[PDB]
Image: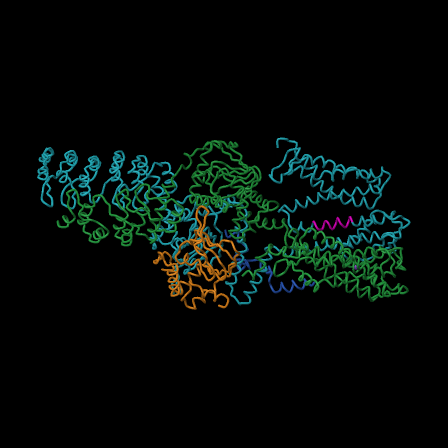
Chain colours: A blue, B cyan, C green, D orange
Amino acid sequence: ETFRWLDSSEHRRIETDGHNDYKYIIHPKNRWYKAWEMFILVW
Amino acid sequence: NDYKYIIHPKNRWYKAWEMFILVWAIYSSLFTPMEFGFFRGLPERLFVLDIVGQIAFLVDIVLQFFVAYRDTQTYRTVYKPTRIAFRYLKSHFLMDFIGCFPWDLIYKASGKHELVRYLLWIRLFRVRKVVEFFQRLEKDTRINYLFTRILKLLFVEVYCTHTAACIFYYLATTLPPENEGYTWIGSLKLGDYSYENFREIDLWKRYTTALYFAIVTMATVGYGDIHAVNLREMIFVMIYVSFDMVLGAYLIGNITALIVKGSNTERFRDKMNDLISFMNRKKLGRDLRSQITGHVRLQYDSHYTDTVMLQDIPASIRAKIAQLLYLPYIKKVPLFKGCSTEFINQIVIRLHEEYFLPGEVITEQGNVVDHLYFVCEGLLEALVTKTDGSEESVTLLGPHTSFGDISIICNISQPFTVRVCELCHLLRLDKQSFSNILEIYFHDGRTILNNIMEEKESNDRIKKLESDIVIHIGKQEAELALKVNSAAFQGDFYQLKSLIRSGADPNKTDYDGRSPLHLAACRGYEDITLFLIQEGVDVNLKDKFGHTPLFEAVKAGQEGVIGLLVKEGASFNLEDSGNFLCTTVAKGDSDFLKRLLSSGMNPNSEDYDHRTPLHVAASEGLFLMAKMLVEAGASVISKDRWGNSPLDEARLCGNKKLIKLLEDVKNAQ
Amino acid sequence: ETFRWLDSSEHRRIETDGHNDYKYIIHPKNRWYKAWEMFILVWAIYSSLFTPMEFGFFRGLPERLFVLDIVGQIAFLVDIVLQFFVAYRDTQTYRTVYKPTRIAFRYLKSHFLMDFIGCFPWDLIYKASGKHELVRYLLWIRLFRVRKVVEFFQRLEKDTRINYLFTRILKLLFVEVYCTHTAACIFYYLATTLPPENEGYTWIGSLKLGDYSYENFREIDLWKRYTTALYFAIVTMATVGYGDIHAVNLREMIFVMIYVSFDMVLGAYLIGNITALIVKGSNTERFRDKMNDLISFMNRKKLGRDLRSQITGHVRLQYDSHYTDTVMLQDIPASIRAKIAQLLYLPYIKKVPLFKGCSTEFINQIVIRLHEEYFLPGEVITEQGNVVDHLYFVCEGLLEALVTKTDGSEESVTLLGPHTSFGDISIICNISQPFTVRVCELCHLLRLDKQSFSNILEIYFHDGRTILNNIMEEKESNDRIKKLESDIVIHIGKQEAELALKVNSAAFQGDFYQLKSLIRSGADPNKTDYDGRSPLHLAACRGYEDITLFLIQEGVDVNLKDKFGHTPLFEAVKAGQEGVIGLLVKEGASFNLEDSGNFLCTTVAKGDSDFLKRLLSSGMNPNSEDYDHRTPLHVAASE
Amino acid sequence: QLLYLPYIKKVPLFKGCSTEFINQIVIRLHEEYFLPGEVITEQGNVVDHLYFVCEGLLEALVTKTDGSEESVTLLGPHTSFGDISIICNISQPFTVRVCELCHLLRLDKQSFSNILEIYFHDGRTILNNIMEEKESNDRIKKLESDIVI
Ligand SMILES: [K+]
């Protein structure tokens, strides 16, 4: 029943999947990925 | 379909011909203004193109005589040829038949008159097929409504610009070539190019020039490099701009109307936007804000189960929906066990789905409830509460359970604040509809009252002969006991059984005793008494007069029902039996006393004076009945309150023919 | 309080003010006067279109068009004096006033002088008074004859056949044109206001379109100058504006700056009214709104592919044809909805063969609780082997009752055409539905519930017995399938066998309203079946009343010996009781009882001074005796 | 208290009541209008609202089975039908039609029972007024309704 309620639900589980491994992957809502998303926006 | 030569309109080989003649009608109604305006008879390059093209619309006329249609008043497909023929001949045959005449060959073989060339303007009764295509596309939910509502308005603004360009060039051709300077194209010079002697310019330069004027005019840009100089072209562009002004206003109106009539996503978006503005204005917390947003998102994503979308669908279709969705969730409920299927079909119609997040509150402690809830999924809990903030998890209401039924039938406030611990799927049912169908179906309300008492063993409120739901049931059960007793009085054995098999009880009594066994025994209907005994009845039931059905059987006189009641526990239990036996000796009806001590009361009982019935029998001379009264009675030595054995009482009667009986029990000592 | 609402009530008072006196004042709905209103509307349309063309394009009318505007002024001079004899359909006091001093007034202080100045000859006055230019500006008074066109669009806005937001669009489209006709006439007049030697500094004297030069422009034909000016004004109104014709003077620049500022507001108002018409949605998008609201809840509930095609079929049936507007009808109260139902359904229910001559109140109670329903062909309504929850009456269409033997042998039992009912032989009975009622043609069934046709069937017991007699006076249902049930529910006694029991249970429970609703409709007996009881034997005494009014009604027979030998005085005195035995004795109650002496000796023997003093106080002679002829003193001296 | 209070003060049901009870009554009223001829209550029904006439000439008639009727009274202004069907929990015995342009004031039965159970001295005064004006032919007891309990 709750699998119908996917995005209308708890939705905050990024904490475990943050830095499992791979050591390079930048989060989208970073701060250095907001000095790029405006610099190359005005580019 | 007993014809086999009539095509169904929803065929898959005919629906490939509709989209073929749609393409041929999109072409042949866009070339027809170009054939009227830009030529004066077609060249020999386009002769074969004009011959086939009036043939694909000539076999379509024949094919429309062999296609069934749906009737408008009976909604049946009409496969009759003489009906589809007379439907085609009176609706669309004439404008499609004279439209596919070879009008160019009729023009060239009539001395080339210009008025026989205006007759090819009835080939625009082929945008009828585009109109029918858009009408079929509007009555199909697979296609979007922003793809259809203005796309058909960006089609009239193609047709009425191409046609206006063709008429605007045609008006330039209506003046002779000596008067070319007084025309819109003859007086035209764009750049270093001059459009003089314009009928030897190639077709696509003239067409692109006229269409450039028509589209720049239609968009109300209007550069004025191309304008009208004549007095016929002034009139035409006045008509044309006064038509495209309201056409552009209609386009802006349709786009604005489909923008201001937004989807439910935008309404929910602005609702969540100003709710988030209220939550950030009031400085709310973290889990509280998530609870508010989750509740309104649950309501938006789950409000689609509202039954007010369905209140034009008829009953026995809404009932089938409610029996497909809700009936397996009501059949497995411990409250409704033993209830008939009619009551459950009346239950499932008036149910409303509800969803709650894990932590909201459904019912509260101090409140009398107004909805009976059924749990489909979820793991709701029941919390009684004290004055000093205490909580006690009394009951864990899982799936297949109900709460609030005790607070409706007994009309009490709710005992438990019901908080929900999971994502639940509750089913509302208001107390008014529940109570109404309880006093409508009282034979199932009695079984509900018997189910509500057991689980709680009536923790309290047990008589609960307080709320009407528990009264109206008592009143209807009483009047149905009256009705089944009237059926049992006269011979209505089939009617009696139809009353009993409709959920009755053959043990509920009348206003003063009077079970159906009582009336069936006093009337002597032996089959009815067999049905009542094998159904299961208290055969020793008493009245407000102190009467058993055995007593009414022996008072009536039918020995068959007398013998039929005594094969079970007949058992008279009659109080004041002594004075009753003495007063039936007093009335002296000997066959009634034969019925009395046949299988019954002991004849050694006593009246207010301590005397046996054989004492009062042997006081006037009643040998024919004193013989009967001495048949089973014993202990003949018994004195009165006066102190008299019945032998010395039988002495002074003055009749000696019953003293012959007095030498009978002289050996039992 | 009808002075507060003179609009909701007192709408059409007609009687006492049609022919008061004066016999001349025409009501403003006469067929001979509304044939003059269209005539003066055509004259007003012509005289308002020709007036700017008379002003701008001429300096005094020629020798022709003289009889034309003479009769144009005569046809309005007639209408000037004709409105002194036309009534005064009023605003606040809703009655057509016939008083011809409130007809001369309300007109003289209104459109009279603007309509009497406009009938003076202003081109004979012009040519008589030395040909002055400012006496020709009084032709513009004749644009007050657009009242007759704006009154036509007010008598059309309150006409319900055409949408009011469409008459507003037609009114704006008659304001858009005639403001391009008047602007064309003023734009040509502003070119004639310059001398003919300064004609090269005008919009038309400095014009050259194609190879034709518009020089010496006062000698061109009138229909070339008018078409040129109107072409400018219409391509300016549409905001196309080619610029082949443009303003040249300052007096033309000022007029174009006024005119495009007026047309911008007018075009924005036209776009707004068209958009306001379109947002009031059509039939197709109001179908598709709830259709996409019902495709979802059919995709997530996972309904079957046949039930989905039935639901979509019924939704496409309530739209696109057969506009069942009960959802609009629900604002109307129950009394007026009952009057609507008695108008619409009584021609159909009275011709049903089930109701062969019942009472009119019973058929009224039937048609109060009816619902209209439409079904496509191929639908199954009531299938064989299920309980019947609704009673259906076929108003129009064609149905089909079928039955199967073993292997789906669907043979046509009957064909239920119009004025037929099905589901009737199983609400009367308590059996299953015996036929699969399938739909052949598009039907219009009238649905009655099962519980309504049990309440109004047990209330109206004479009509219920008439309905059972209508069912049995048939071929005993061998026209259908010969499913004979006994003889239906047979005569089941609701005359005396259950109604005396019903009124006796009403007396036993103590319901006075049910008691008097039963007995004031007749049928007050003195006997119960299955016993010798009475509505006096129950209520009065044993119950001891509940309700004090149980003894005064109808004066029923006291001293009725029941099946167990108890008079109602004995039942009132056994339960002791002290109101009915105080009250029954003045009504002539008696203590008749067989072996009363033996009963008194037994009440001596048990010992009950209250019981025996209530026996003796309510009338009892203690010299009656028993089988041994012993008085109650002979046993009250025993122990 | 300035729109409805002169109407509710001169009601024979609320005679002798405290002014605070009337001030609690007048808040929950709903102004209603009816043209001369509709029906607002029927023959057998426990009524859902208590009404007060302000300017109107409603009639209260009892219907029979065979279509007939007779008016037991003529409810003019400053009258209150309803209440005896509410506070005795019985059905309203009269089909209350209307003969003029009436000016009723609704009051639902749950809120009326709430104000009666909170202010019980005025409830006893209302019970006394109904027991003398209806004359209390029976149910001087009237413990069938939980309001009196
Ligand atoms: K322009």
Camera sees residue B483: yes
Report the side of C243 relative to C332 (left or right).
Answer: right
Report the side of C169 relative to B557 (left or right).
Answer: right
Q: Position of residue B274 (x, y in %)?
A: 57, 63
Q: Position of residue C475 (x, y in %)?
A: 47, 31
Which segment is the magenta one? Answer: B152-163
Q: Count up the numbered dots.
A: 0
**In the image, residue B552 above or below residue D90:** above
Q: Position of residue A8 (x, y in %)?
A: 54, 56
Quick check: is B285 in the magenta stretch? no
Q: Nearer the viewer, residue B307 or C524?
A: C524
Q: What type of secondary structure mainly makes up the magenta span?
A: helix
Q: Nearer the viewer, residue B366 or C352?
A: C352
Quick check: is B156 in the magenta stretch? yes
Q: Position of residue C473 (x, y in %)?
A: 45, 34
Report the side of C235 relative to C379 (left or right).
Answer: right
**In the image, residue C335 above or below residue B651:** below
Report the side of C109 relative to C230 (left or right).
Answer: left
Q: Quadrant of the N terminus of chain C?
A: bottom right
Camera sees residue B462: no
Which corner quadrant of the figure contains ligand 1?
bottom right
